[PDB]
Image (cartoon, rainbow, N blue to C red; front, top):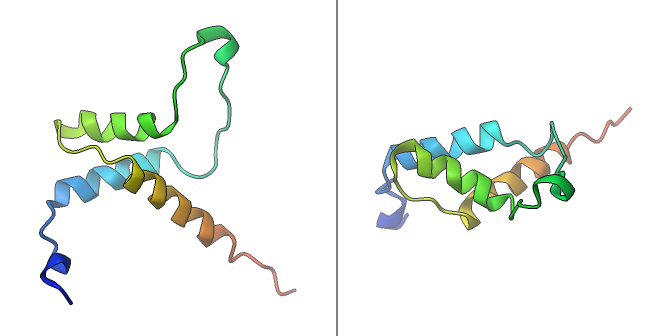
Length: 82
């Protein structure tokens, strides 16, 4: 249990993460009409934009992408044993 696991990170950061992960889940909506707007960069920028609007605090993108991938693993455990 290194000192790094002492929750040195602010709780407002980890909180803003759930807000972006809660707002942007692994499912619910999948559309991107680029033919019209012609301006739609990586979705990772959408999750980072949220945390950036929280309080101008950090805005991790790789950490917010990894968190969304973890949610997909929870759905994979829905193997109906019948």
